[PDB]
Image 1: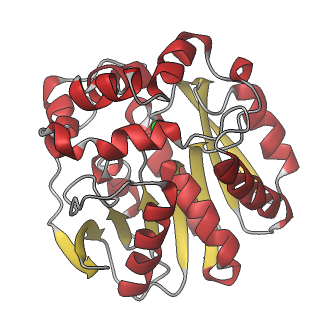
Image 2 (image 1 turned 180 degrees about the vertical axis):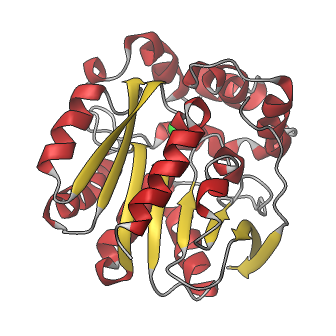
Length: 292
Ligand SMILES: [Cl-]
């Protein structure tokens, strides 16, 4: 049975006038490992992978601004907002060199930070990450009508903000195996008040789909161009059928990206961490040992 508890002691750092929550476990020496979550999760999504890495490495998993146990100021919560906060989070913790373990929107932050700081990244493990979606035909059929609704200010805000559809609908429909009530309540916890659900709506409105928004497509195309050139060791977890990364796209990127190893986790949609945390955690620890 996949674990449901969150036993990590809370840590907080002040940043741009707000406090951000982060997990900090493992031995201090070595290269720290930085876990970046996405929408609509938090560091809770890493709770069963970190125990495979914490024996030998320091594990840092922050809650994005406006999410988890972090502060929730009245922001627009655009992707630029998360960039400015994650930039100053990494600097506030004195993280000189890091290994990235990123997912969903945490991967957009991780890849964009790596492009701007390539000398400070010693490895990138990633899964179901932000890539350009050329047309809506490359988006999964069963989720197309829902995400097109999300990307409007009338229907999309009614579903995500008023009815909490991204937590009540999108989250369980992004995991193959059934979630428990305790696991749902952990994801419901940061967004009990509808006024705090702004990040849950802006994030899908930022997804680079069909060239829109053009500023996010351009940004993702740049760090995807840097990925193809960089020699940084890469670990690519993928699931079947997946959501953002279909198996065929993972097969192409495993061979086209330099020093990229691909791992099949079995059945999976978007939250691969909830479908096979033991394989993901153990494969990260093994892969870290082959980098020294
Ligand atoms: Cl999203």
